[PDB]
Image (tube, rainbow over all chains, first blue to last red; front, top):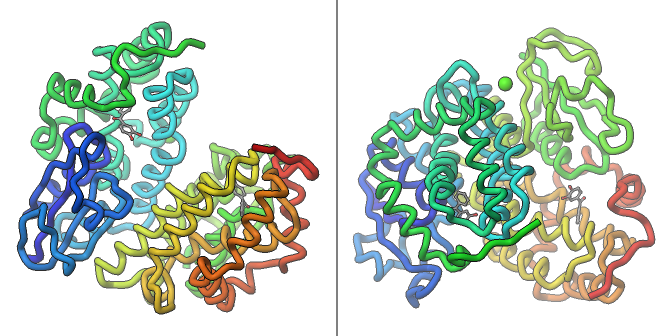
Length: 241
Length: 241
Ligand SMILES: O=C(c1ccccc1)c1ccc(O)c(O)c1
Ligand SMILES: O=C(c1ccccc1)c1ccc(O)c(O)c1
Ligand SMILES: [Ca+2]
């Protein structure tokens, strides 16, 4: 019954992680867009002093999201939010109950954060070579149960953590979005279509097919347009070897 | 009941986190050193295919650590391990029960991993400027309850996550260890002694005073020698501006 407000942006996969979890929770919550990259409201640092999206307020008196109460708890960092939601809504079974399975969920998330996420940001925002990113994705793909299903077996917050980035990768590639080079983009599109990456394609499809995804995605074409407003995605800039 | 073997190195702060947590659990567990950087046993990828320390085996038959059994669960990534130990050992209260307090533990861990750890690695291993690391450390300091106590109030795994790195910073500094410049080392030495960093010094003292720390620390002098066996701490190499 305590209110949940999530500060978001359509383009952001970090915000997207938490929307997905909140859906799978059957939670009652508010979203409120913030143009964090070009025109941050003056009050935002009151919900997140790091000036990053997502941000979350919890509890306090019901207020307009742009008039945040100093009495709500201010919760930062998307993976902290996913664990918080799981904690709040235990009947939703957002993590398994078995600790080894819970540890598969947690291990999967740290593999994404520590070895994959930095390669996405680097290939896309700096044009660094794609090969290490393909290697990190092959490594992450091997963590999945190879006969089907989600990271921990049943769906968990670990699948919320990773799908925003993977589901963005395909339509961004088809749209030539990113600073990497044409050579590397052909290389990425060929690899993500080859058999090497069949398992991960299944995983993207499986996650995409859940309502939590469909209800938090504006559409492939719409998301590409949202991503275009991202400065560092300097439209028509490419870096070479 | 089921066995826990943790593959470690004295130098490694990531391994150190799991030792601290296992102590606070009152867990029965085995440690087995692995010279991961110079001479990795060729069985080691059976416990961790990423070839990193720490690695953990859980359950299966009692075997010698260097004859790991295919039937034990293989758990990777230190923060997944900390969450796993909290799960296994709930009477130990390694996390609070209140969700918002639990979210402060998780937020604190993400703040360290996302804004602080990369700056330690870069100042120390690449000689990059100290300033962003001091700024990140100031931000992390502000997340602490300023009146005293640990990240989430009571001690939690979030404190295991962070103290191996902070407790190393001070004696490594005094020992002139790292690739950063002399100027930068004087700068970090002064900054970490000034009143700006009073709170974090008390947090380091608070954490160090627990048995979990003392029983997992070889001694300041010993740990500095252990750190010297690290290639990327190539003694007598320094980078400037
Ligand atoms: O959307 C992405 C992304 C990048 C590459 C592939 C797929 C998605 C992204 C956006 C903001 C970030 O700060 C970031 O690290 C990543
Ligand atoms: O020991 C440290 C360290 C570095 C700087 C200050 C204090 C401790 C370390 C060791 C291996 C790593 O991979 C790493 O990122 C960090
Ligand atoms: Ca596998």
